[PDB]
Amino acid sequence: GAMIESSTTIQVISAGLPRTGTKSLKNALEIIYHKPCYHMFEIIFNKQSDIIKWQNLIHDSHMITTTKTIAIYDKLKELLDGYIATTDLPTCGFYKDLMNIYPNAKVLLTIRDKYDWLHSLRKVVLPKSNDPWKLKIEEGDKVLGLNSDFYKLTEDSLKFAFQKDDLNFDDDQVLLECYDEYNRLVQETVPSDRLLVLRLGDGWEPLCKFLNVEIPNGIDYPCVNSHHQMTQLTEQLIKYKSLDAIIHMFPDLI
Ligand SMILES: Nc1ncnc2c1ncn2[C@@H]1O[C@H](COP(=O)(O)O)[C@@H](OP(=O)(O)O)[C@H]1O
Ligand SMILES: CC(C)NC[C@@H]1CCc2cc(CO)c([N+](=O)[O-])cc2N1
Ligand code: NA
């Protein structure tokens, strides 16, 4: 196809929850658009200074209906300046607001089997409080410079996505119910013409068709960020005590 000059603004809003192929999708969108896509990894590896800003936004987000709405929307736009898409926490819970701010953006929902999702979440993002692996995650997190404010953001952005005032994070049934309800609500809320639902394994074709772009030539659809790979990353951070000592060992993930 012909090369055209794409606008550096949010063109794709992905409402999918963590552990549903968001990092692969981030990578895929960057391959298509040649500009950055937001993701939790953007915060962890590039913009830890954003943590307090997302926290403040979530804090004020109950006021979203107006005057207050504009201030909140201004802060969201600021956070996303220079990006062409959003994926993952903390952004995904803001999908409705993002649709208002970026009326010409299309919306994606990444989904998968709910028990596979939960298993993956428990290994990487939200281990049970009595799981010994939680201590290893915390040790690796310290190597990356992530502290309690990072955990607060993770929890608060999950609660915001699930529209809960509090949440028993150690309760699998609660998390599964929230997952199902969240995915159902996205599909009820977003007009179908504006939504593409992507199941893990769908690859380039439906995505590129939805976005009116050619499938990237000779490039396989990304497959990164398995829980196994994250377990290796955690162990290597603990072993070497820095990111820069091992970053070359994780080329597409980081
Ligand atoms: N192209 C692909 N095909 C199949 N699974 C993929 C995939 N890309 C990512 N995944 C899976 O999506 C999950 C990561 O999602 P996210 O980036 O949102 O955290 C991982 O699940 P597992 O942990 O079950 O391996 C990963 O293996
Ligand atoms: C050792 C270190 C790599 N641990 C950091 C972990 C794993 C990456 C990660 C990813 C997400 C969402 O992609 C979230 N999240 O949903 O808040 C939290 C975390 N925290
Ligand atoms: Na990258």
Image (tube, rainbow, N blue to C red):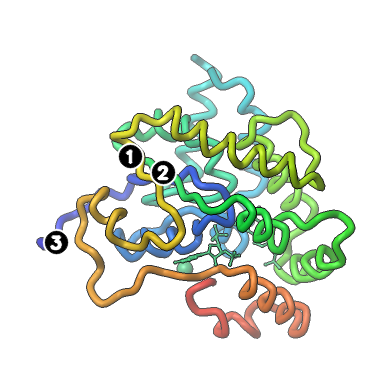
Residue 147, horizontal then vertical, whole percent: 78, 57
Residue 240, horizontal then vertical, whole percent: 74, 84
Which quarter of the picture shows residue 64?
top right
Residue at the left extreme of this rendering: 2
Residue at the right extreme of this rendering: 130
Q: Earlier in the sequence, mark 2 or mark 3?
A: 3
Alpha carbons under labels 2 and 3: distance apart: 23 Å
**Contact between labelled residues 1 and 3, with CB atoms less than 8 Å apart:** no
* Above or below: residue 131 compared with residue 50: below
Residue depicted at x 48% and y 34%: 186
Residue depicted at x 75% and y 65%: 141
Alpha carbons under labels 3 and 1: distance apart: 20 Å
Read off the residue under disc 2: 13
Query: Which of labels 2 and 3 is toward the front?
Result: 2
**Contact between labelled residues 3 and 2, with CB atoms less than 8 Å apart:** no
Per the image, label 3 sits on a secondary structure element best described as loop
Read off the residue under disc 1: 105
Alpha carbons under labels 1 and 2: distance apart: 7 Å
Q: Earlier in the sequence, mark 1 or mark 2?
A: 2
Under mark 2, the amino acid is Ile
Residue depicted at x 63% and y 68%: 227
Residue 90, horizontal then vertical, whole percent: 59, 45
Read off the residue under disc 3: 3
Which quarter of the picture shows residue 156?
top right
